[PDB]
Image (tube, coloured by chain):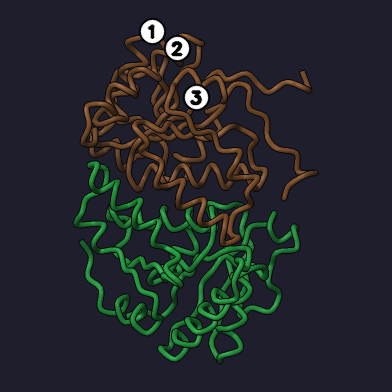
Chain colours: A brown, B green
Amino acid sequence: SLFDAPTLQRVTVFTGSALGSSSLYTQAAQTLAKTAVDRGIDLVYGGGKVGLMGIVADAFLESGGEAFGVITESLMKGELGHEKLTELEIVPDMHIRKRRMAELGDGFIAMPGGAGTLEELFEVWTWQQLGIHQKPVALYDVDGFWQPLLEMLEQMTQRGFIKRDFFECLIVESDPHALLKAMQTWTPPAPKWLE
Amino acid sequence: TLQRVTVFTGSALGSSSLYTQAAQTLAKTAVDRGIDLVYGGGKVGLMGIVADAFLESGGEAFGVITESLMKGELGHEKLTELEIVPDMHIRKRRMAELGDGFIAMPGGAGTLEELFEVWTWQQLGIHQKPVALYDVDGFWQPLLEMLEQMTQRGFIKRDFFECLIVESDPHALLKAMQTWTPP
């Protein structure tokens, strides 16, 4: 229906190819995967087998959900792709990879990661602002990991480079049930009233 | 050597005229070095400011813009050359091909997005070009603080974070770019 948000069938997850320095990030990813599958949401992600990327894909498969990785030729030649995925799309470059992860997902989540995770997050958020998609964008704030980013965006907003209304449409939860609940009920803000 | 530099900067002007001025001063400094501008082709915000400044100072400015943004009345019509491309990704492929290095002046989410793409791709060996942050009025300090924590939590190689250029003065910035070596 026209008044309804599309219902989330898949979520695209951005996260590190390292595990990072707390056991907690491995736990927290596992929990989200379980919650996701509980609501019949499947996973789209970058197709890796190590670090949090690997953790989250494995947790998804193990809870009995599905998992669609999208990976490049370069990465597949260097034999870095996960081998037991529901599907694994191999594409010529990093652009197409991001484009395809964004077409496949019904929403985006950023779990802890580094530069690459930021590359992906800001792109999809920018695109939301340009009207290229109207899918929700969320930060999984595991042990406050994303708090420094929020301080940075708050400062950018104050200096006038980001509209407060966009920044406030960013979902940030540390609880996974909350996170996905906000993603399901999310609607984009009316262009009619931005300020 | 550095002949063209790709600049990422905000589509708005920001709440203080300091940014406009720094953007102007940087363009002059780069023209004096013989360096031309490559950027996303807009006339609004600091994009417009920096492109005007390169032109008015005797230098050249090349824009790469999508068909959509052109249609949106955001394009600059008095550049040295303006390429029109299908989409955002071809636009970044081209800005990266044309650039010999990358500078991120103040901006928002659009700027962040371009910045992180080319930084990440430096980490992966896709290119070996300097990436620099023009730290006007400490604008990028909160970003460095975020990166510092990510490095302390295991998600960014310290080695790589240290190869990131950060400078508030434009003569220092361009010299840092000119003498930089890869990680």
Kind of element beneath mark 2:
helix
Instruction: Tell me the residue that label 3 is attached to.
Output: A179
Measure how far apart labels 2 and 3 are at the Cα level: 14 Å
Residue depicted at 42% across the width and 28% down the height = A174
Going from N to C along the chain, the mark reached first, 2 or 3, is 2
Measure how far apart labels 3 and 1 are at the Cα level: 21 Å
The chain identifier of the residue carrying mark 1 reads A
Kind of element beneath mark 3:
helix
Residue B171 screen position, x and y as percent? 37, 85
**Residue mark closest to the camera, 2 vs 3:** 3
Residue depicted at 22% across the width and 50% down the height = B157
Q: Is residue B89 left or right of residue A50?
A: right
Instruction: Tell me the residue that label 1 is attached to.
Output: A64
Residue A165 screen position, x and y as percent? 65, 45
Discs 1 and 2 share one subunit: yes
- Which amino acid type is shown beneath numbered disc 1? Gly
Q: Tell which of A57 and A178 is nearer to you.
A: A178
Q: Is residue B3 above or below residue A17?
A: below
